[PDB]
Image: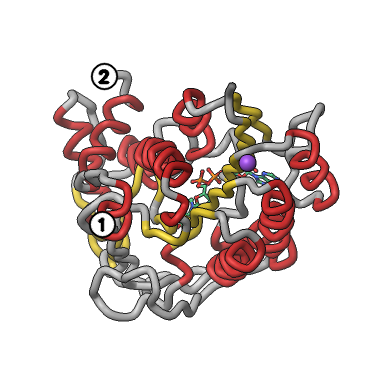
Amino acid sequence: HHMKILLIGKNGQVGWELQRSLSTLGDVVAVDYFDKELCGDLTNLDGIAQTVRTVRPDVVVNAAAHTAVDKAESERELSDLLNDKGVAVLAAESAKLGALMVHYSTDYVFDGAGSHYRREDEATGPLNVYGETKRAGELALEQGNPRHLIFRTSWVYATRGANFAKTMLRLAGEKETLSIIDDQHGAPTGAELLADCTATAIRETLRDPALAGTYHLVASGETSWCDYARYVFEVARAHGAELAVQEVKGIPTTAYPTPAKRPLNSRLSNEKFQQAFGVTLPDWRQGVARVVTEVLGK
Ligand SMILES: NC(=O)c1ccc[n+]([C@@H]2O[C@H](COP(=O)([O-])OP(=O)(O)OC[C@H]3O[C@@H](n4cnc5c(N)ncnc54)[C@H](OP(=O)(O)O)[C@@H]3O)[C@@H](O)[C@H]2O)c1
Ligand code: NA
């Protein structure tokens, strides 16, 4: 017998790696909003509910979200649908089936104060619509399905998809100088790490259901966006890439404002996850070096 796993958001950065990592846990039914047979559109509340009822999963993994942080400030209804109302429907339908539901969240549920690595039960206080609707979805899942795993993560990148590492690598081909924010700090976390630790956590939580709850799932360490970009260029040049960029200048968040206010401290303690699931979470540089290498075809 094989468990039935429903993956929503299959085409995203994390969803694509979950198509790999979940494939040995059971029979995977993977959808995204373009699917024609099953509704994979998390904003179609009745349709996505019918998909859960049809598939009857043992595990639901939601990798779909509204992730365009600055656009979210002018798309508040859509952000609420994708990050809150849709998550509530998934929680209700999965709990009717007794299914374990996995959901991802964000460092942006916090206000960005301090310089410490945040523990999971600190008070939330989002500064932007993305964080507000993401936190509302967290609460909807907590109330709707006790059998859940919520993984807060940060600064996600991958070989496939759009992200800061690939954007920096492209811009470094063309621009001689880059001005990059140096006062926001967090851990770049790879879609690979998120997908593999998710599969591990699912297996361990099915074995020990007491492990349900909320975890910070990030790579270890911290960097500013500025030093992150510098590292991407260091790796690229070590693999023979020719880059135009000569200087990366650090600038404060106040220098050029964004529609969405961003937290300065995005550090998340990942000790709870390591202890609960018996995993090592490597320093953030490793996963970034790997993606840069793959993007360059090396
Ligand atoms: N700030 C953070 O902490 C941060 C950063 C990255 C990711 N995350 C979280 O980690 C999870 C995924 O990470 P990601 O990096 O994979 O984000 P992503 O790459 O944007 O993947 C987003 C997924 O949602 C899909 N989607 C968009 N509109 C949809 C709809 N109406 N119905 C169904 N699916 C829809 C996207 O498809 P299209 O893109 O083609 O619409 C894509 O498949 C999300 O929970 C996200 O919030 C958090
Ligand atoms: Na069951």
Question: Which residue sits at x=39%, y=47%?
Answer: 164
Tag 2: Cα neighbours inside 10 Å, few (<14), some, or many (≥20)? few
Mark 2 to mark 1: distance in Å? 24 Å
User: x%, y% of residue 33?
Assistant: 72, 38
> Which amino acid type corresponds to the residue marked 2 in the rendered image?
Lys
> Which amino acid type corresponds to the residue marked 1 in the rendered image?
Cys
* Element at label 2: loop
47 versus 211 height, above or below: above
From where the camera sits, is residue 152 visible?
Answer: yes
Q: Which residue is mark 2?
A: 298
Question: Which residue sits at x=42%, y=48%?
Answer: 208
Question: Which residue sits at x=50%, y=58%?
Answer: 105
Q: What is the image's colouring?
A: secondary structure
274 versus 251 height, above or below: above
User: x%, y% of residue 121?
Assistant: 39, 74
Residue 213 falls left or right of residue 295:
right
Residue 210 falls left or right of residue 267:
right
* Element at label 1: helix
State the residue in front, 248 or 25: 25
Residue 199 falls left or right of residue 76:
left
Whether the residue under disc 2 has CB within 8 Å of ligand 1: no
Q: Quadrant of the N terminus?
A: top right
| Mark linked to residue 197 | none
Residue situated furthest right in the rendering? 46
Q: Which residue is mark 1?
A: 226
Question: Which residue sits at x=42%, y=64%?
Answer: 107
Considering only order in the chain, which callout, 1 or 2, is on the residue closer to the N terminus?
1
